[PDB]
Amino acid sequence: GRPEWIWLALGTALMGLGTLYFLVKGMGVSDPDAKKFYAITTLVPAIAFTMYLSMLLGYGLTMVPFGGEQNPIYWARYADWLFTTPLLLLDLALLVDADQGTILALVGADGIMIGTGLVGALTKVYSYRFVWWAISTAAMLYILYVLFFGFTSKAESMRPEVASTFKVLRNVTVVLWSAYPVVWLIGSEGAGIVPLNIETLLFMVLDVSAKVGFGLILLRSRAIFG
């Protein structure tokens, strides 16, 4: 019925395929630190797979009325990102051995980031749709600031393998996460200049890269081993 069913279907496969690949790659691995990373990394694409699968079958999609139009809103993405993104943050947290104080702030910021994002995607007053977007973006920027400025300094005190792998995951996270608030802004959630079918394609390339590709880079590395 909806033309974006194919992109919902391509993500499902890759996220499902990456789920087992990480799950398979995680078998027999004895290192305790690695077991932590494999479990976290493997659960993320599994969480996304489940929501990509439900959307493909016509679940988690509502029609929010704003801007004079009935705008189709995929609210299932927020149940996905609510758990996948904090695990991506915890992955970096364990990677750089950050103290609990930083983590609570990162996890708190992510909840507000994804929390407000869903309200804006469902608010019926148009203007406030963008108000909530700003708060979320403000939250995201705080996260990227901690990762870019805080975490990096810690990664250098570590051994070289940890620093080299974190920089790649930092640049991948910074690049991909920064793209999420813009697509939301111009897409069906806000402006309505990019049709919903295209919005879906851009979120998939990011999610896959921000999970499968992100996970792939992490679990192919020797830094997860203590």
Image (cartoon, rainbow, N blue to C red):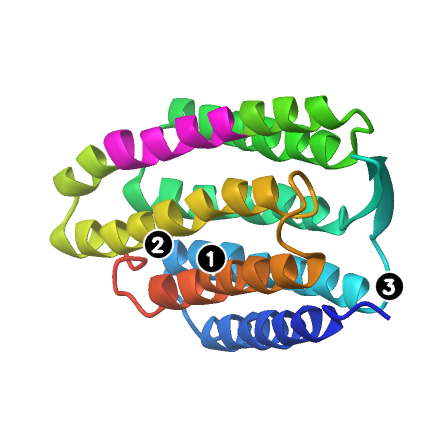
Q: Earlier in the sequence, mark 3 or mark 1?
A: 3
Circle 3 packing at 10 Å, graded few (<14), some (14-19), many (20+), is: few
Comes first in the chain, label 3 or label 2: 3
N-term mark: 2 or 1: 2
| Tag shown at residue 146 | none
In space, the residues marked 3 and 2 are separated at their CA atoms by: 31 Å
Magenta highlight on residue 156? no
Indicate left or right for 65 with 18 as reference.
right
**What is the C-alpha distance between the residues marked 2 and 1?**
7 Å
Quadrant position of residue 127: top right
Q: Nearer the viewer, residue 28 or 72?
A: 72
Above/below status of 56 relative to 85: below
Q: Amino acid at mark 1?
A: Ala
Q: Please state the extent of the stretch shown in magenta in the rendering.
A: 137-151
Dot 3: element: loop
Labelled disc at residue 58:
3
Element under disc 1:
helix
Q: Identify residue for label 1.
A: 210
Mark 2 vs 1: CB contact within 8 A: yes
Regarding residue 98, the answer to whether it shows in the image is no
- Going by the image, does 2 lie left or right of 194? right
In this image, 85 relative to 28: left or right?
Answer: right
Residue at coordinates 28% horizontally, 65% vertically from top-left? 221
Residue at image mark 2: 172
Q: Residue visible at 41% across and 60% down? A: 214
On-image quarter of the C terminus: bottom left
Q: Are marks 3 and 2 in contact (CB under 8 Å)?
A: no
Q: At 57% from the left edge and 31% from the top edge, which residue is drawn?
A: 113
Task: Kindly indicate whether the residue at mark 1 contacts the one at mark 3 (C-beta within 8 angstroms).
Answer: no
**Does residue 195 appear in this view?**
yes
76 above or below 43? above
Mark 3 residue type: Gly
